[PDB]
Amino acid sequence: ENQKQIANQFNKAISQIQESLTTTSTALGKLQDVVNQNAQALNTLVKQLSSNFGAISSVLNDILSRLDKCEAEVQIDRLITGRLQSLQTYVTQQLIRAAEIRASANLAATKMSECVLGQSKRVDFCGKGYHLMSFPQAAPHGVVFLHVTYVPSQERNFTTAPAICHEGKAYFPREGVFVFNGTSWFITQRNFFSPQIITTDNTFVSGNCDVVIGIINNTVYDPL
Amino acid sequence: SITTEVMPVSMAKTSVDCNMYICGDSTECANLLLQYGSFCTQLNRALSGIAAEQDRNTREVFAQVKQMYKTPTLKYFGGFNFSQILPDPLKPTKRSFIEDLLFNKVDLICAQKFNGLTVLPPLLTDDMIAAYTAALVSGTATAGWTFGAGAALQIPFAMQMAYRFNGIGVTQNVLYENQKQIANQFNKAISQIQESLTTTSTALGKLQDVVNQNAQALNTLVKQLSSNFGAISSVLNDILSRLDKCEAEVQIDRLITGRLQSLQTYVTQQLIRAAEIRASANLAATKMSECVLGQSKRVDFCGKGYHLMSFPQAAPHGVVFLH
Amino acid sequence: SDFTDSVRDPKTSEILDISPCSFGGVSVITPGTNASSEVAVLYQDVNCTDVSTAIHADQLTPAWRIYSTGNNVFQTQAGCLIGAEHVDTSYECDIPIGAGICASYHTKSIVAYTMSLGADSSIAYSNNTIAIPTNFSI
Amino acid sequence: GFNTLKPIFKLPLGINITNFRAILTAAYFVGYLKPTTFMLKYDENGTITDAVDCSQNPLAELKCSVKSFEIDKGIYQTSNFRVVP
Ligand SMILES: *[C@@H]1O[C@H](CO)[C@@H](O)[C@H](O)[C@H]1NC(C)=O
Ligand SMILES: *[C@@H]1O[C@H](CO)[C@@H](O)[C@H](O)[C@H]1NC(C)=O
Ligand SMILES: *[C@@H]1O[C@H](CO)[C@@H](O)[C@H](O)[C@H]1NC(C)=O
Ligand SMILES: *[C@@H]1O[C@H](CO)[C@@H](O)[C@H](O)[C@H]1NC(C)=O
Ligand SMILES: *[C@@H]1O[C@H](CO)[C@@H](O)[C@H](O)[C@H]1NC(C)=O
Ligand SMILES: *[C@@H]1O[C@H](CO)[C@@H](O)[C@H](O)[C@H]1NC(C)=O
Ligand SMILES: *[C@@H]1O[C@H](CO)[C@@H](O)[C@H](O)[C@H]1NC(C)=O
Ligand SMILES: *[C@@H]1O[C@H](CO)[C@@H](O)[C@H](O)[C@H]1NC(C)=O
C-alpha cells in the first residue's frame, strides 16, 4: 500500500552512510588497531637489537673485533640467549593475537552465513530492530555489514481485553490483540495499527466466560 | 521451572612495577636493568591491555539498555510475584534479595605491595552493575520484547505470557483458563531458589575459581623472589654487601634474568586466562541479548524445556541468569 | 620473599621496621600535551589525610608540593585525586579513573565527576492498556 | 632561557679539587651539580636540542616514563623519578 515511501527511506538511509563515512575517520577504529598492533610489535622487535644483555657491547662485530675466539664465547652466548628469548616472546604474542583474530573471523563467517544469505530471527545479532536483509562490503583486512532493519515508531495508547464473549462462549484472537477506539472494539496486529473489524474467522472459541479474568462483553460479526 | 545459570564476565585488573620487582630500591641494579632495554614497557603494555579489556567486558555484558527504567512501586503483576528479584525500597541495600544471597557465597598482601604488585579497582562499582539489572528486570515486567528492539511499549503481564505461549506452540487459551495455577507455580519456583542458594555453596564455583586462580598466580609470583637462580644468595642486598663492582656483575645478572623470565611467564599465563574470560564474557553478552530482551527458539541455549522469559542478576565478577 | 622487614640496632638493642622509600602507585591524567600543560595526580590506595607522609613531600621540589595538598583534593575509592575540580553533575565517561569516577577537560580545566549510567526515564504499568505503533522507519 | 654547552677540553691532571676561586682584574653565578635523571633529544647533526628533567614535575615524570615529548589524552601510570636517597 505504501511501497513508494518505503523505497524513499531506503534511498535516504544509504545516502546518509556516505555523509557519515566521508567526514569522520574514527568509524573504522577496529581495523586500524590491528595495523597499529602489528607495526608496534615488529618495530619493538627491531629496537630490541640495540640492547646488550650484560655483554660488553650490543654490536656483535665489536665483540669479535677486539676479543679472541676464547673470551668472546661467553659474550656471544649471552647475546644469543637474549636475542633468542626476545624472538620467542614476539612469536608467543603473535600466536595469542592470531587466536583472537581467528575468533573474530569465525564470528564474521557465521554472520555472513546467517544474515546475508538469509533472514535471522536472533535478537540483536544483525542490528537493532527487526532484521530485513544485509549487504557485505570489503575493507582493509576486514568486512563491513550494512544491516537494514525495521523499527516501529509513533506509539499510540489503547485499552485492551484478553477475550470477549458473545453468547456465553469466549472468543480468543488468532493473531493480534483486541483494542478499543472511540466507540468500537477492533482486532490488530502488534507491530502496526491496521484495525480490522472482528469476524468469526479470525477468532477461535474455547469455553465459557465465567473463568477468564477481565472479559468484556461485545458482539462478533458473522459472515452468514 | 526456573533454572539458574552462572557465568563469569571479568577478572581482576593487575599491574606490576618492573623496576621495583626486579631491583627494589637499588641504584646499581637499576643501572644494570637499563641495559635490558625495552623489556618492561613491552610487559606493562600487555597488562594495561588486559585491564582495559576487563572493563570492556563488564560494560558490554550489562549496558545493553540506552534508557533506564525505575522500579515500579507495585511488585505484583497479575498474580506473578516479582518482589523477590527487584530492589526493596524500605531495605537499606540497593540490591535484590537474591543478589544479596549471591554476594555472600563468593602478611601476603603486605608482601605484594612492597614488591610493586597493585590490583586496580573496577570502573563500574557493585551498586551500578546492580542498578543496570534492576532496569532489565523492570523493563521485562512493564514492557516486552521491544525495549531492546526500539521504543519500550507497555503491556499487561498476563498478555505478555500469552504471546510467549504462542512462541512455543501452545494456544493462548491454555494460559487464561488456568492463570492462577501458573502464577502459583511461578511464585513457588522463585522461592525454591532461595532455599537452595542459602544452604549449599556449590553453585557459584565458576566465580570462585577465577578468584582462586588469580590469587594463586600472584602469590606464586611473590614466592618466586626467594630463589637465587644459581647466584650466591637470593637477597640482592647480600650480594652488594660483600662483593665488589668487578665480581658482582655476573652475580646480579643471574638474578635479573631469572626474575625477568618469571615475570614474563606470569604475563603469558595472564594473557591466556584473559582470552578465555573474554570468550565467556562474549557468550554472556549474546545470552543476555537473545534471551532477556527476547524469546529464543534455539534448543537448550537458555535452559531445559521451552523457553518463556529470563531475568539477569549480578554476582561477584559475573552474571546469573534465571531461565 | 627474601626482603628484610626489621633489623636490630646493634647499640641500643631496639627493633626497626624497614619499608621501601616510595611504595604504592601514582598516576597522571593529562588532556594531551598539545592541549594544555596541566595534569591531575592520583595516588592509589592512599587516604588523603596522609598523602604528604607517604610521598615524603618535605624532600621534594616546590613544583611537587602543589600536587600534595590544596583546595582541589578529592577522595575516591581508588585513592586521592589532586588537581581536579570536583563537580556534582554527571556526564558520560571520558577518562576512566576507577570506582565510578571519570575525569575530563571541561569549561578550561580538568574536572572529575561521577559517570552517568544512562537516560533517566519511566514507563507506567496498567493492567488494561497497551501501546501499539502506528508508523515505522527503515 | 636554554643553551646547550659543547665540550671544549678534558685535562689529564690527577688531583682532588674541592675548592675554587675566580680571578678578576660584572658578576658571576655558581651552581652545584647533583645526580639526577634527564631525558635528552638528539637531532640529525648529533646535538642536544631539547631536554626534560624527570624530577621536576609530575608531567615531566610522565614524559620520562613514556619516553616521548608528546603525550596523548588519557590516564597513565608513572615510575619513581621524584625521590633520591
Ligand atoms: C499513554 O498514557 C500514559 C498515561 O496514561 C502517558 O504517560 C503516555 O505518554 C501515553 N502514551 C502516548 C504515546 O502518548
Ligand atoms: C479509532 O479511534 C479514534 C479515536 O480518536 C476515532 O476517532 C476513530 O473513529 C476510530 N476508528 C474508527 C474506524 O471508528
Ligand atoms: C486492573 O487493576 C485495577 C487496580 O488494581 C483493578 O481495580 C481492576 O479490576 C483490574 N482489572 C483487571 C481486568 O484485572
Ligand atoms: C511475594 O513474596 C514475598 C516473599 O516473602 C512476600 O513477602 C510477599 O507478600 C509476596 N507478595 C504477595 C503475596 O503479593
Ligand atoms: C654501646 O654504645 C652506646 C653508644 O655510646 C651506649 O649507649 C651503650 O650503652 C653501649 N653498650 C651497649 C651494651 O649497648
Ligand atoms: C584512612 O586513613 C587511615 C590512616 O591510617 C587508614 O588506616 C585507613 O585505612 C584509611 N581509610 C581507607 C578507607 O583506606
Ligand atoms: C509516517 O511518517 C512519514 C514521514 O514521517 C509520513 O509521510 C507518513 O504519513 C506517516 N504515516 C502515517 C500513517 O501518517
Ligand atoms: C645538520 O647540519 C646540516 C649542515 O650543517 C644542516 O644543513 C642541517 O640543517 C642540520 N640539521 C638540523 C636539524 O638543523
Image (cartoon, coloured by chain):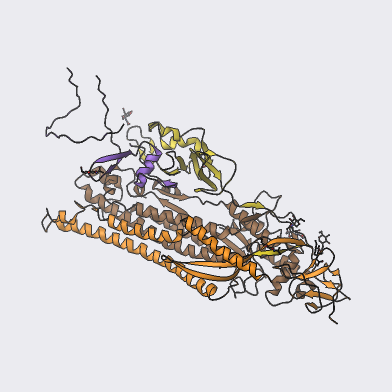
Chain colours: A orange, B brown, C yellow, D purple
Residue A114 seen in the figure: yes
Determine whether, in the image, residue D9 is placed left or right of residue A162: left
Decide which of A221, B263 is in the foreground and name it.
A221
**Hey, which residue is sitting farthest bottom in the picture?**
A224
Position in image of residue A104 (x %, y %): 46, 67
Q: Residue visible at 43% across and 44% down?
A: C32
Residue C4 seen in the figure: no
Vertical placement of residue A75 versus B146, above or below: above
Determine whether, in the image, residue B63 is placed left or right of residue D59: right
Determine whether, in the image, residue B47 is placed left or right of residue B198: left
Q: Quadrant of the N terminus of chain B?
A: bottom right
Q: Residue visible at 56% across and 66% down?
A: B286
Report the label total.
0
Position in image of residue B200 (x %, y %): 60, 63
Decide which of B224, A2 is in the foreground and name it.
A2
Position in image of residue D40 (x %, y %): 29, 41
Position in image of residue B90 (x %, y %): 71, 49
Q: Residue visible at 57% across and 71% down?
A: A133
Vertical placement of residue B142 versus B112, above or below: below
Decide which of D12, C126 is in the foreground and name it.
C126
